[PDB]
Image (cartoon, grey):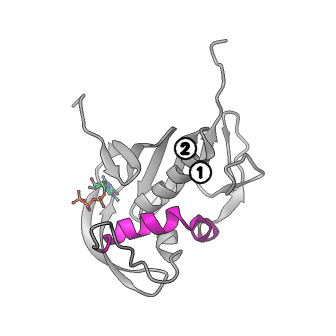
């Protein structure tokens, strides 16, 4: 239907544009050697995504971020959107990136649930994530360019992530 409330994953705002995922509770052995109970989504899905000023298209499958296209925006929003999408995608690389205990409390003194532990952890320790994520030679394409961990156009890109330029197509 035309009017749809957006879904939210902390700071990440999302709207699904294709696919049909199904959620199954699974036990996941993550990178710090602990087992986490997580509702894992299965199926190829694409989302419209946004964090602050940065907007993009996220394509995922089960525990895999396939492709992330985003616009150029303020670097903190670009970086946060990428991290939130890596976490949202439940990518195995993301799970494997965790070190030490994820036992963060909220302001009501309760433990965050596992997905929110992960969002909180990687937002504030992104080098853990990006190291595990992998880098590849940037795509050489006309309207797309890769980005590095500093959110700059580079010869090498975070794997699966692509940025568009702000171009005056209509003059
Ligand atoms: C990883 N997610 C998370 N998610 C949805 O994104 C929102 C934020 O996830 P969440 O806060 O972990 O949801 P949760 O607390 O598990 O509640 P729910 O029972 O709705 O899943 C929720 O609306 C959740 O349903 C998703 N929706 C789809 N279609 N595919 C997905 O892979 C995912």
Q: Secondary structure at mark 1?
A: strand
Q: Residue furthest left?
A: 1
Given residues 73 and 170, the one toward you in this image is: 73
- Residue depicted at x 70% and y 39%: 141
- Residue depicted at x 24% and y 28%: 2
Separation of disc 1 and disc 2 at Cα? Answer: 6 Å
Q: Secondary structure at mark 2?
A: strand
- Placement of 143 over or under 163, stated as above or below: above
89 on left or right of 158: left
User: Mark 1–mark 2 contact, CB under 8 Å?
Assistant: yes
Residue numbers of the magenta segment: 111-132
Lower sequence index among marks 1 and 2: 2
Report the disc number at residue 69.
2
- Residue depicted at x 27% and y 68%: 108
> Which residue bears the numbered disc 1?
161
**Which quadrant does the N terminus fall into?**
top left
Q: How many residues crowd around disc 1 within 10 Å: few (fewer than 14), some, or many (20 or more)?
A: many
Q: How many residues crowd around disc 2 within 10 Å: few (fewer than 14), some, or many (20 or more)?
A: many
Residue 169 image position (x, y, % from top left): 64, 18
Report the disc number at residue 24.
none
Is most of the magenta stretch helix, strand or loop? helix
Residue 126 image position (x, y, % from top left): 58, 64
User: Quadrant location of ligand 1?
Assistant: bottom left
Given residues 152 and 111, the one toward you in this image is: 111
Q: Tell me the quarter of the picture where residue 163 sits.
A: top right
Residue 61 image position (x, y, % from top left): 41, 58
Given residues 74 and 26, the one toward you in this image is: 74
88 on left or right of 38: right
């Amino acid at each position: 239907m035309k009017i749809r409330q957006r879904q939210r994953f902390g700071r990440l705002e999302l709207k699904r544009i294709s696919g049909r995922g199904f959620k199954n509770d699974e036990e996941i052995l993550i990178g710090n050697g602990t087992i986490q109970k997580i509702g894992i989504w299965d199926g190829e899905e694409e989302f419209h995504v946004r964090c602050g000023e940065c907007r993009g298209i996220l394509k995922k499958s089960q525990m895999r971020m396939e492709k992330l296209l985003i616009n150029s925006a303020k670097k903190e929003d670009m970086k946060d959107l990428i991290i939130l999408c890596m976490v949202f995608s439940q990518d195995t690389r993301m799970f494997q990136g965790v070190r030490g205990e994820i036992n963060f409390l909220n302001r009501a003194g309760q433990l965050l649930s596992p997905m929110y532990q992960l969002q909180r952890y990687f937002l504030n320790r992104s080098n853990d994530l990006f190291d595990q994520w992998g880098y590849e030679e940037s795509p050489k394409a006309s309207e797309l360019h890769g980005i590095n961990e500093l959110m700059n156009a580079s010869d090498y890109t975070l794997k699966g992530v692509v940025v568009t330029k702000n171009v005056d197509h209509h003059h």
